[PDB]
View (cartoon, rainbow, N blue to C red):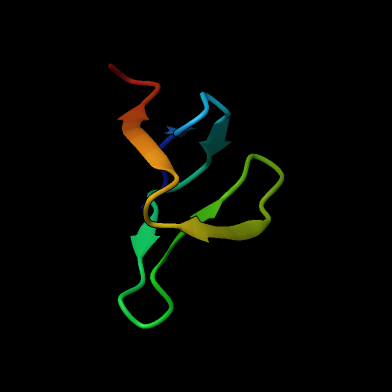
Length: 55
């Protein structure tokens, strides 16, 4: 499934994903696919708010 989701970090840095993120218990990161179609991962504590563009 694909849906636009903007993840806002602790400092306020917002990144927009084309599909929904995965919380990985193994490494402790959140995995999300950026607008470019590139998957990136950031630590569980850096994420402030997880919201869709469809609010």
